[PDB]
Amino acid sequence: EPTYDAEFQHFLRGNEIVLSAGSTPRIQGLTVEQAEAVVRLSCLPAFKDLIAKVQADEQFGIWLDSSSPEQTVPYLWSEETPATPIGQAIHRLLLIQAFRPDRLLAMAHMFVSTNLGESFMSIMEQPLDLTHIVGTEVKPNTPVLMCSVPGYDASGHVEDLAAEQNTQITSIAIGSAEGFNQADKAINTAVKSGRWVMLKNVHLAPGWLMQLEKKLHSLQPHACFRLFLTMEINPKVPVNLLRAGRIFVFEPPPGVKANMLRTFSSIPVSRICKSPNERARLYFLLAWFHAIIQERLRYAPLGWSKKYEFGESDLRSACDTVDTWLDDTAKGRQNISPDKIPWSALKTLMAQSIYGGRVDNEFDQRLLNTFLERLFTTRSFDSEFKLACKVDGHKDIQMPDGIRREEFVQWVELLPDTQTPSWLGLPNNAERVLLTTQGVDMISKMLKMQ
Amino acid sequence: LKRTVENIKDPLFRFFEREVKMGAKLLQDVRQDLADVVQVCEGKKKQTNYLRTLINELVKGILPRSWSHYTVPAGMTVIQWVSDFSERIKQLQNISLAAASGGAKELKNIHVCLGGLFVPEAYITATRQYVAQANSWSLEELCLEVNVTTSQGATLDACSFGVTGLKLQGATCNNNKLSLSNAISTALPLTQLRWVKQTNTEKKASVVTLPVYLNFTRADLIFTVDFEIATKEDPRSFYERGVAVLCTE
């Protein structure tokens, strides 16, 4: 295969090519940006006739508006000899970059599939199999660093693995000077006895982590000894410890459905089951609310002006507020009418105290007010309420008609797996925006590696 | 720009003079840096520590910290930065030539792209001050209105200033009325910013107060614009949709 140095050079620095002012023509069906992209791509010798071929193509528009153009990119590049499959792949990559950058990542995946195998990326699209990795690919003196994005805890994976393997595990939370002594004693015991040690939230102690790395460099651990360090991704973790450890990055699975499931699992069942019976429905709305603001953070700057830290602490505060207000209003009644729910108190508090405290932009505050007013209202208790209207422009999502926690949990479990931005109120093309941003985020990253 | 006694009274001249000063200084900085880089690539100049860091950034497409002195999107490559530089300097050259030829009076009739200014908020304040000085009204009593005109050569009123380069995210403007659209962005044509005495007019239910962000990151807010809704669409849909306006894409 030839190096394809020129084509990759255009792929990474095609924008570096200069277009003279007024040199960009108008092409039927292409926007201004696609016109600049095609003009830049025409510099390469293979795509010299690209503009005329694009103009002459009757079936171009159906390709340009297609949902999956990368699978059926048209043949436009001129070739003196028939190209290899990888040559076709890179030419299709250039065409997709020029016309539909939003699909570039998908096209990139195909290029990987064209070069390194179809199942190459598949093994990562799977559940993490910590058992074989920790048993075979990890030495006892190499600590397993489980890093999570903030607000996500991964100690459950280690506890599940310890349960599966039938191995005693000692877990210590590092949050005070005492925890350092407990960790040192536990590690000194396990290194000799070959036990498993877990240290939770070690990002809070950078200097002690440097000391632990220096200590680990000198030990002669037992074969069955393992040291897991669970932390959140922060820059204060020592570089040497990351260099001298096995890093596993855990992220939450994106989607409203998983978010609601995590929220319901985190809340104790007794808290939701408490009287009056209406409380659970409010929790469901609160959960839905916490999902809608959170997933929307993926689509910033469109979803929010900036990435706020709407974490679990806000959810716990909201739950405490709901509990206090319903306890005050109901006074122990098994049931209260939907009208008697203090809707104004909840709307104001989650608009200014719980979630609005982090919001500094006035426009984001207005958006939060709109969401709270749309969701927290007496009409939420009507069977015909719509959590999200015109989903995909034609369909809608209805409130569950149940009253118990189990009914809401089943409704969440039965939600469709196919989620679009219209669930959160954003337009569908917001997804098309996000991908292209990530698409640029790919190329620029590769430029830092070139 | 040639400062004089007569033109200094114009707020527009003060704003453009400050812009030209900052642009010229940054222009000399970038030109010297690029000349040194080309000299290094030819072997004429040795790689100093600052120069070596500059080659490290330029080769990787990173924007050097030494070049960023006005607000820009974070994570921008260098080609976009120098292209925006060329556009901004061309705009500054055009406005400077207009000032030299017709004096400060032409600064009102020139169509200024707020994207091409290092601080367009100062331009908005300057237009407000110019209207206040001309019509002898207090600054507090002036309020902003926007007219989107597709006609070429739409004459500007004494209190109206032209703008170009605005982009409307999430909506299409027809007949000076917004409608929700699935297009990612729509190029606004010549936009007339008009300052009017704040009449005690009830806020119409069909009026939506969109922001005007500096760029696509939406980190900086320049001002807000009230627009009328074409259909019976809920204004809340514009808030949920995140409709907004950007001075530059």
Image: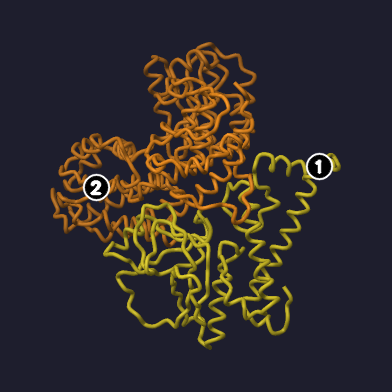
Q: Is residue B58 left or right of residue A99?
A: right
Q: Which quadrant is the N terminus of chain A positioned in?
A: top right
Give how far across and how far down residue A386 sits, in percent. 22, 50
Q: Between residues A68 and A332, which one lies in front from this camera angle? A: A68
Point out which mark residue A85 bears: none
- Location of residue A324 with respect to A96 vertically, above or below: below
The answer to whether residue B222 of the structure is visible from this angle is yes
Write down the chain letter for disc 2. Answer: A
What kind of residue is marked 1? Answer: Val
Q: Measure the alpha-carbon separation of dots 1 and 2.
A: 61 Å
CB atoms of marks 1 and 2 within 8 Å: no
Q: Is disc 2 on the same chain as disc 1?
A: no
Classify residue A189 as left or right of residue A402.
right
Chain in yellow?
B
Q: Colour of chain A?
A: orange
| Residue sitting at the far top | A223
Residue with the mark numbered 2: A394
Viewer-nearest residue: A393 or A175: A393
Percent from the top left, x then y, of residue B142?
Answer: 47, 80
Left or right of residue B93, residue A278 in this image: left
Question: Residue visible at 86% across and 42% down?
Answer: B44
Q: For label 2, count other residues whose C-alpha is less than 10 Å away and answer few (under 14), some (14-19) or many (20+).
A: few
- What residue is disc 1 on? B40
